[PDB]
Image (cartoon, coloured by chain):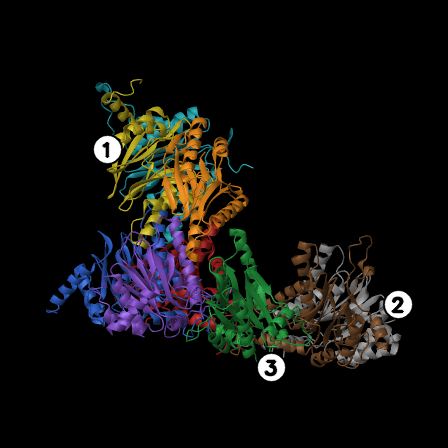
Amino acid sequence: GSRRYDSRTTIFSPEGRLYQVEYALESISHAGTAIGIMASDGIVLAAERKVTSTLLEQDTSTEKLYKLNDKIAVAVAGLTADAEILINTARIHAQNYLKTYNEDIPVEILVRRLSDIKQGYTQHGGLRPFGVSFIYAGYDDRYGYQLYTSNPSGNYTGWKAISVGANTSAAQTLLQMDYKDDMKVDDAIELALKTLSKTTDSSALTYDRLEFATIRKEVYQKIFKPQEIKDILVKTGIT
Amino acid sequence: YDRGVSTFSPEGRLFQVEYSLEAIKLGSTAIGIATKEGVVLGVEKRATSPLLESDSIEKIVEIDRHIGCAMSGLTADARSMIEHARTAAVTHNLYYDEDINVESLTQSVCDLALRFGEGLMSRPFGVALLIAGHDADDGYQLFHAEPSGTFYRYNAKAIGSGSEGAQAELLNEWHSSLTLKEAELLVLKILKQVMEEKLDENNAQLSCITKQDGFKIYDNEKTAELIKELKEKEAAE
Amino acid sequence: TTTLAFRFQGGIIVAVDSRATAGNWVASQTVKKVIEINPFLLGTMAGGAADCQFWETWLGSQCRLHELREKERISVAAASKILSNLVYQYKGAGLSMGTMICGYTRKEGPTIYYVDSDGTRLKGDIFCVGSGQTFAYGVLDSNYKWDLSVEDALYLGKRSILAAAHRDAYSGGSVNLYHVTEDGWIYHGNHDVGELFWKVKEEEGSFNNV
Amino acid sequence: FNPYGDNGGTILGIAGEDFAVLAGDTRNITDYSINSRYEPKVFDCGDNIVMSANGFAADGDALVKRFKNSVKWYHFDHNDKKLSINSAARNIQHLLYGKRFFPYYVHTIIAGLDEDGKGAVYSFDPVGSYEREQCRAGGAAASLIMPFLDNQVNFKNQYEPGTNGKVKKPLKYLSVEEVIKLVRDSFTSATERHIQVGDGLEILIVTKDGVRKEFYELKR
Amino acid sequence: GYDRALSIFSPDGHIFQVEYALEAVKRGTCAVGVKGKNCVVLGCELQDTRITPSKVSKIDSHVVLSFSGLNADSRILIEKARVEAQSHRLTLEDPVTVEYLTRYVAGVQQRYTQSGGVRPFGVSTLIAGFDPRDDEPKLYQTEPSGIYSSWSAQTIGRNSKTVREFLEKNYDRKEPPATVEECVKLTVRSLLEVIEITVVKPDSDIVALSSEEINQYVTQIEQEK
Amino acid sequence: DRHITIFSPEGRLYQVEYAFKATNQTNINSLAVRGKDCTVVISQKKVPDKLLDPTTVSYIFCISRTIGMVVNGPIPDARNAALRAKAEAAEFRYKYGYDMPCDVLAKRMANLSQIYTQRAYMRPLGVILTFVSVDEELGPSIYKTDPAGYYVGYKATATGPKQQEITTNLENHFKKSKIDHINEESWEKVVEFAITHMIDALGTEFSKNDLEVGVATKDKFFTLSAENIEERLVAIAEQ
Amino acid sequence: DRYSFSLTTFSPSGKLGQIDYALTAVKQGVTSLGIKATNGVVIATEKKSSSPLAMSETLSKVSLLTPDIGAVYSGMGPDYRVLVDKSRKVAHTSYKRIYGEYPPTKLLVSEVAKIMQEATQSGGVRPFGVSLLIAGHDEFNGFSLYQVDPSGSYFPWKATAIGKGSVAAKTFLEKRWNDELELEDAIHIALLTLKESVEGEFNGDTIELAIIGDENPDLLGYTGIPTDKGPRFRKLTSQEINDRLEAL
Amino acid sequence: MDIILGIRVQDSVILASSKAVTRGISVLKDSDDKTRQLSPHTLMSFAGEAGDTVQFAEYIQANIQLYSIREDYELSPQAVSSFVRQELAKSIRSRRPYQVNVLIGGYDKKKNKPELYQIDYLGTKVELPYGAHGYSGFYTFSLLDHHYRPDMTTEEGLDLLKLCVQELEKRMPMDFKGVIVKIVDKDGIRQVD
Amino acid sequence: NNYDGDTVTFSPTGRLFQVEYALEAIKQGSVTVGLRSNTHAVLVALKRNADELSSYQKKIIKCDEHMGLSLAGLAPDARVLSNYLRQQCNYSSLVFNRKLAVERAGHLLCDKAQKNTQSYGGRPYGVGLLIIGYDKSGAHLLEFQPSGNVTELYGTAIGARSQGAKTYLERTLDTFIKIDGNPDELIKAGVEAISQSLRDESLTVDNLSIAIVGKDTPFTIYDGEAVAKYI
């Protein structure tokens, strides 16, 4: 039968590791760096675009950052098509929760459900895992601003500042070096862009290679237009 | 994984059944002795640490008032088998207003065993059962139920890692005129022999089935009294 | 038909009639309207006989499986909820049931749950069910006490069934008495309602109209 | 469409101390027409169990067929062990209640010996409630048959003649021959007064010695 | 659907996937449990602490689950256990016993060792609590195989061999720790043999200790050694 | 990768290529040509076993009143395709109220072939299908379908081991005539042309038993009996 | 079907091998290109004949998906044909039947990308061996040009090329493209870019070109609804292509 | 029929529910509590078809308890009433509707506000200062419309409830065997007379 | 051997190795003899015990008073097939009120067994059966093999060393086929046949079981002291 061709995803190695999860994580280590920083007054999301050309519409490409609802955004590293599948599921879940309770979904509930979807593919069904890591930025009235990450295993963790993708050891080193709990969103914007600039493997960080977003106080949720990215890059002295 | 779970060896045996039998050789010893007065079951409670509460191990279980089971091997697999057996016994009482025979229950469990494959459970059970009981048709009966889905009635049987030595001693020392007290002490004797630990009321557990009161597991105090009695009488053997 | 159960210091009395009818025809005088679910649980058949008998015997099976799994007697609350959930799953399918689940456990003490085809589940001290229930209530509410003797409680049960048998044509035949104790239920025998009627009529002097 | 009909017929189970009788008339009717004068309704089901499922005859036939099959399967999976009358009664309850929502429209009686060797009669409603009884009539003329048997077997309402109603007439052993005589007279009176009560009476007698069959002609 | 027999016997009669699930447990972060006479104490050694809560999850108000191994798999077991606890409380009239819940979770793990197309859970759990009208503390372990057993003290995960040898030296099976302070001190001592502490007490009295209390124990231990 | 329809590192589907090899197993050549208002199919018939009933040996199928199909490749897969095509055509007429066009049927069968190229559990059929009709709108039509799920219309076509020799001779004829069709008013002369051209290409004379001939006209598709082929062959001998 | 498992899996280096192999199939395909102007989009491809006897007119490499959205491909033609059928159906069932409106280009591209992604993860299927260029117009976003790859990743482009010649073509398009380019200039540049990659014969029979442009009320087929727009998609005839090539 | 009444005062919600249970000809019980605590600060009372009411209320209670365990958090009375409304609105379209009318009284500890929601078996939800189901409103709303003040203390609310109950006892022909009274406030749920 | 991994694979010579290995299961099983006359059919089975303390495993299963079988090999497969045969006989009785012909029962088993040889995921049965019955065409004996081959025979033996008994039956056919009045002499012929398959073992009231069916002889199993007459 077909047993010959089954690669047997969802098996343990002798070390008790899930090899498809480890290899999907390797895949994500080649994706464009994304950074989340939780300020006192908000959250910054920043991401590097790996695909670049003069002929790309950077003004309409929106491949790294997505709104999940009015209060929650994600940054993506990895396979954008898999991410779009999961993002659509999360959007539906948030609206189902609002329909049921007439309240906006708590950020952790959304993150947990999407992480559980990712876990399922590691345990049953014989399919490959989703090759995406997310950073979730959100606000809710229970914990306020919250920053989460999740990976192909369906593990999720809360962070004050976090990086996913290529340069994350360097990024987390620089974030440990410069992060402070008191820092404002305008401080965190600088820290994010300085970390991307110091971690990018390109020659220089430029507004076409960037996506940027903020969640700040109601809560407003801004994806930066490229001119705003120019403004912020000159304001930070990076361009 | 190369080979499908349902395949025969060239010798005409199912590989996964054979390997399940290899799993049972690793299990802790269970011993059954049938007598005209009752069936005794004893088990080695192979505690892995002193912080383990030996009283939670529960390798002997009631299947019905006059039917008990001792397990050896992958004892987590036994819980499904015992759930099925208990359901069968209760369902039989529901449908016929009478107790299930011990043999019909053993068959019900053995019918479960080869229902594994693909396209059903993924594998055989890794556990052997000694099924002891009483019924009015055939009296005190002991059965060995095996992951092959075969069973035999036994006068006495040992299963698990001690089984070959214990069974050789059962071949020596079983006889039809054994009293239940003699079966109790013979079980304790052979456990003590094949157990690596010193036999005591914490390392081992006993039970019997008698028609007057059914299946009961012996408390540690009674077992310690019997182990003392064995230690006394061993002076003359 | 008439069935009753009441709590007292001695536990629970269950009293039932044995009449069965088909229109005006008396089909049987000797129906057992108490189902002995197990040595510790009783149920009372007052709906359709088949539904009560079948499902309370199955309830006994579920109690036995629970005891084997959990190594403990099932609660009367648990048994009555198992039954009421089953009956509710067939709501509108046309089950006909009206039963007191009676038992006495250490955690709960003597407990009665009324259970209905409609899915009602009521705990209570006293219940009377069937076409004669109002006559039984009339005696029982007039005469019930918690401190009543066991023999007085059995007599009160018998007299309430007798009152129904006198007035309700569909009740009678004989009285079956049960006494639920912590140690289990005790059957206190069968009492023919005609013998009982003429006895009480002379000894008590009641039914002067007859 | 009505999936039910009435085929008439009357049946009578009597438990003795060491025997059981199950009797039935042999006429099959539809409305005012005779379908058959000898269509037997009382069957030896094996294991010295006799059965009759009176009412809608297609459901009665189906239930008897299924019970006989249950007996065969019980033998297959119990090494031809005898089925107890009590276990047969429980199994028949399960057969009937499996049709709870489209019932077998029959009153069933089974008869046999209990494991003490005493006569046993069990009666079942269409839905499967059942009771061990000393006696049960079923079908169209049950009301014509049973009061007389209550009077003659159980001496109901009979008092010891000199005692002016103080002392009951004492119960005593009826032989199977005395029971058969009472059954014959009861069915003869029902034949006189009920238009459905048949052209013949078939009696199955269960004893330690097995099942024996007696037939008596009724009028018409 | 996908039905591949993933858990199968090897020729020596082992089930490699269950052994490798145990390797996943052994790599997983520690969990420690110490049962006293009147409480069970559970402990563990740029993250946002508020939203990286205790690994000790309530399954119901009276019973608590810790785990070692794959965190994501543990979320699945915890959700199933919570649902079963509420289901038992609904369909029957009582909260679950600790042993009933343990048996349910061990059954779930066992079933995933014998079911087509599924991996075994790379999880071991400690289940601690009190039965609803009982004051004997309970501390059970489950394993990927679906074995479960009761323990007086136990450790699972990374360092659990060393910590278990320490508990075997220092826990007295015939003189168990008599107060919450003694249980906590023993738990912290065992964890320092290489901090977060939950105390479980009767009547749904479950309390995470403050870090300032734990540091009090830690400094006392470091002063007495 | 060699065994199932997944990509090789070169992006090839080896099982599809090998299914093309199966199409020549029968060593039969077929030829189709368009007239002004007919389409003709010629196929070789090779019946070496004297015990065969030659009337049962055919690779030409009547799919509908109007559509013929000739198959190159083993007869079991040919009969599979023929049955499916017949069912599709009848179902189309039922659903849509008009006779299925030859090009639409060829598209549908090509899509089924593509499914076999994309789903691992079904092998390709080892057949090349040539559909012929006179379409109500397009007129005389030849559409040829292959194991890749490719199909196209043809002015004329040949299939089989010697298809290059027949095709190059046809191409030279169209170069000689500067037309997209055979300029003859009646199908008998198109049959005689097609036979003559197959003879010239293969270098072999044909007996009436060595050929089978299908003709699509506006009214119907039909297959010639051996005696009608005799009449055409003697016409060639005398014309 | 016993192939319930994924045939595309991660290698130890994190590659999805089947997707890279599908991209190799695409890169060997016949060159296709797209150019967005201020006032339209051009998509163009070579029509390679399989035979001089084949009627290349019967094979449509450029397909209307909606009146205002067109697609072209490079790679496996049959996979493209099946994706076109699915895209058309999903444009109806997922959008037109709900909103009474044809989908915007980006949302239809998302639906196609979803279909392609599912072939990279669902049981028993290989990826599609095609890359698509999807050109469209919608009222709010205007003209759009997207590339969809076998992974189901998609990117908006100002201009791009796919297939065997895509490197030289993309370099030429970077030379030639600008923000002020009108559709006639884009067509001229498209024809130049294909000329440098066709296997010699270059004419309206060997080229397929379509535009998204002005509404074409003559193609609408009815009159009397002033709000009903004519289709913006239009395939150029071979004679229009020849007329432009003679003036090239 | 059953009486359930609710009054939201300044600091608390008062729920009052009739004690009678009647089957056919007889009052079986005179002490029945027609409420379930959904959460420490949320109480639901229910009225309607026998069996349906308790099956529904216990299903809701189990789901809210499960949510609280999963999140370690208490849903607002708003979220609870939305969930209950959704379950009732589903049931209307189901194969056997729950014929159950509920009042949900809760204290929102984030807003520090009492909230009273009335939900009919159709899933018609309305937040109200005071509420009733069936005929109880026909007799009580004119008293509440006349006397109710939003700033009432709990004690004034209870006195107004007493007037409503006295009016029901006077004019309503059934004997409902009085009411159980529960108060939901910042301290939780308590039973009162 | 790359070809023995499943039933759906032919070897290059057209063998089905999993079927052959399931036949090896039968060859490892203990001997059963079947033989018939015109009026009676007999089964004789040597049971094996696990050890001196075990019971002897049942070799013979009644289907009906008109039919029954004996097994060699994997006894749970014999239980499956016996239950299926019981269901088929039951269905024939319930629906047609006719006794199922033994030949048709055999073909029903053939068809059930063949499916496991033709499709993936199952396995062949590991058990050979000897079926005896009496019907309107008289006494019948069938041998079932889990290749699905069923053959009607006057006599045969299956299991280990069974070729000795088969040789004896071949040698004595013209005698035992005539034994129509005398079921005990047909049983004795079968017991003498099975003796030719014994190695270093003797027949006892413990290890020997017998069945017989025939004209007025409902299928009956003799075991224990009931076989002491025939030893």
Q: Which element type, helix, strand or loop, lies under badge 2?
A: loop
**Can residue A8 be seen at all in this image of the molecule?**
yes
- On the picture, is C186 further left or further right than D111? left
Palette colour of chain A:
green
Of all residues, the one furthest to the left in this rendering is: B236
Percent position (x, y) of residue G171? 71, 80
Colour orange belongs to chain: H
Of tags 3 and 1, the one toward the viewer is 3
For mark 3, what is the residue? A203
Write down which chain is painted blue: B
Residue placed under numbered mark 2 in the picture:
F185
Q: What's the residue at 51%, 61% (across, down)?
A: A139
Residue under label 1, please give it.
Answer: C148
Asked if residue I50 is positioned above or below residue F199 in the image, the reply reads: above
Q: Are marks 3 and 2 on the same chain?
A: no
Q: CA distance from mark 3 to mark 1?
A: 98 Å
User: Which lettered chain is shown in red?
Assistant: I
Residue G86 horizontal/vertical position (percent): 67, 63
In terms of secondary structure, where does tag 3 sit? loop
Chain E as rendered: colour: purple
User: In the rendering, what colour is chain D?
Assistant: cyan
